[PDB]
Length: 127
Image 1 (cartoon, rainbow, N blue to C red):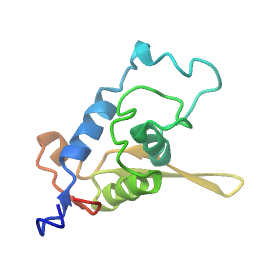
Image 2: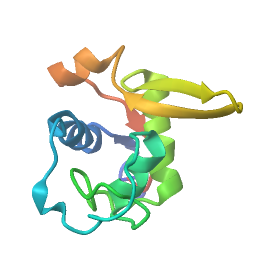
Image 3: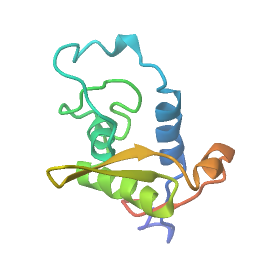
Image 4: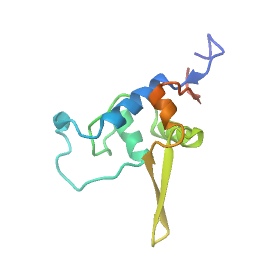
């Protein structure tokens, strides 16, 4: 906690919590209830962001929903984007024939280290 410590935050506790939910999200919690109306969605980094905070754009309500409510959406973005750079996260760059690009979320390169739990990356917030 940079104010007492010179430490910056290793988002490993944060990230592992994220990973747990997304990994076990091979199914979904039926107790989600809320958005049981409307069209489906896709799993992209920014969707996970809105979910992570417990925001209300999010249409999933299962997993890390309202678990990182101490972040701001663009801060959470910055992290999933830190993760894609570190390669814990791997971004699925997809563009349709309208030159509209969107990136999905998967874990690829450092993902095995995530499973081993030895994944320790940094992130800078108020810690």
